[PDB]
Amino acid sequence: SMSEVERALDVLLQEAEELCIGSSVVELDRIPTALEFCREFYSKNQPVVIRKALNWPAIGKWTPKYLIEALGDRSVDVAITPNGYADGLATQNGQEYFVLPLETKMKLSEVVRRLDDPTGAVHYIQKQNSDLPELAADLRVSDLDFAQQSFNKPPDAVNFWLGDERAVTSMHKDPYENVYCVISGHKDFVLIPPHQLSCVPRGIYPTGVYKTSDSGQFYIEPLRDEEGSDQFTEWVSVDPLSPDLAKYPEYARAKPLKVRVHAGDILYLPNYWFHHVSQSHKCIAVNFWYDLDYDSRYCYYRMLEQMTS
Amino acid sequence: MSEVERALDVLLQEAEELCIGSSVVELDRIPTALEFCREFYSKNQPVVIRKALNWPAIGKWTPKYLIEALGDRSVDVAITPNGYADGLATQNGQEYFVLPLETKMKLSEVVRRLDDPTGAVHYIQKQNSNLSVDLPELAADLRVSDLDFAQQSFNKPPDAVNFWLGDERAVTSMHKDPYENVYCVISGHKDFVLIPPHQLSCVPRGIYPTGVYKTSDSGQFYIEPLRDEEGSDQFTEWVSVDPLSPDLAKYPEYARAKPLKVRVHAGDILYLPNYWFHHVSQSHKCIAVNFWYDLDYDSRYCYYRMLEQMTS
Ligand SMILES: O=C(O)c1ccnc(C(=O)O)c1
Ligand SMILES: O=C(O)c1ccnc(C(=O)O)c1
Ligand SMILES: [Mn+2]
Ligand SMILES: [Mn+2]
Image 1 (cartoon, rainbow over the protein chains, first blue to last red):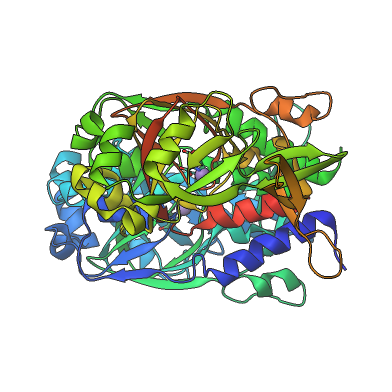
Image 2: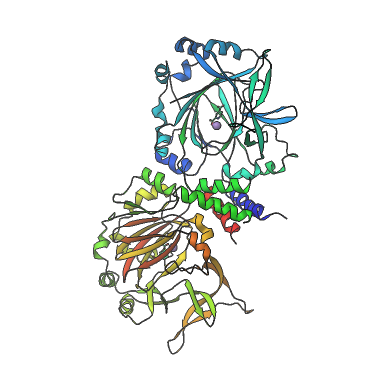
């Protein structure tokens, strides 16, 4: 038999199984109305993927070469890793850390050159925007009103991504509503619903950052507080691509959803959904992050965090 | 405190600090379907809209006009001695959950009994879609299309439409319904006390023998316990507290609860979201109608079932 907290958790999971909560990513051929989106997806905290939804100029024009021609081969901020796991788990001297990317700057064409070398380190570009007007002129952001009218606030962030196939984003959650638009290539998402939290292994790890030495080899440097001892972070311990079900029995009761998002597709990723992200080589994407509007679901989720701490 | 009580403390802290289910929103104008979906339905948040309806009914529906328009036909009426149909009452040392005495009588007969201050409490409260079922001719004095602003968020027709006409002594004890509720007062006013689902742990609940009101040959009311052949009580889980006069010594947990009071006048619309606890009083001969819609399941319902397991 099981504990009191575990009886409560089991009731949650059984009720959500019977009702098939978060059991499928809805597939749409056409952009829904603002009301359809509010009713069927936003208010139900439910992912949706809209196929061939966008006809943006970008979708054709945008490549690394065209971006170099357009942006004037500017200097950008790029994240670098030895293993391709920025914000991810890595071992050193037998200790598993949560490591942050080595963040540096370089010329866009140099980034492109370093993307074509399989032998080198893994690079990805994540630009946190709000030349740049020229780039914004290749996008019809109004096409996303159907979703924005549900959130009733402007994008709190608009990110541009250009990255290596080797760049894998490990499973994590975000306090945002997320509208994701692939421009070039395809992005693979693995999604787990919030309420399955108790089936997702999480641990506490010393946090570090990747650094190069004089010789150019990578190591992990522990991160430390204002003055004194180490810093920690809580992070998903399981690998969705190859779950070790022996080490993590409970993960077998989870139900991950797999969705591939192609150029011209839209993916609504609701707030606090677990996701793991892969992509094709030199995939380009832009996504819009909206601050969430707190409802009782968030409070239940905080409670669930407390129960499964 | 235990792990479960710690988790419940988290739930209540976050909800209180984020102003979740913390008030009834007043509007003077009917929202748009999108506004209603975003601000009230998707948030499971109650809202009252003042002077929202201009139905013919709001002018004309009285005891007399209903006696005339319905040809003084016979109707279902719930009767109690204390005014608590489907409520708790004590007898011979035992607290029972009591079902009302249900009978049929002429509409004019009911009106005569509402005019008796000393009589038993009468209430036309059958619900189970008694307006569409038993009173179709009244439907022409309403305009259900005016509720489209909310109906589009439910995306299904009303699964029930109820008609209420009761005594000021007829009080409905606190309970929850598996429905989205659109409440339209026609005459008089209705007083609601509301508590959000996530405060379930602040609401005491008990298992009670079930009974039903009966009269003796002399006309005295009494509770008859409901039992099967074996002599065993059939039980009902019910809210134990009286929102009007809470007994915080008996029920300390109700201290952390925050009831919301709202009076709904003729022409006002109240949206009572699914599984919201509600207690209902009314003015004398208040007339109301309301529309029940089956709820659309999401993870909140699973969390509420977990909350019920956590507090039993
Ligand atoms: O595209 C990504 O690599 C990525 C990484 C982390 N987060 C997100 C997101 O859409 O939230 C996307
Ligand atoms: O108006 C009432 O008396 C009443 C009683 C019980 N329930 C409801 C309801 O609208 O759910 C209304
Ligand atoms: Mn993310
Ligand atoms: Mn009710």
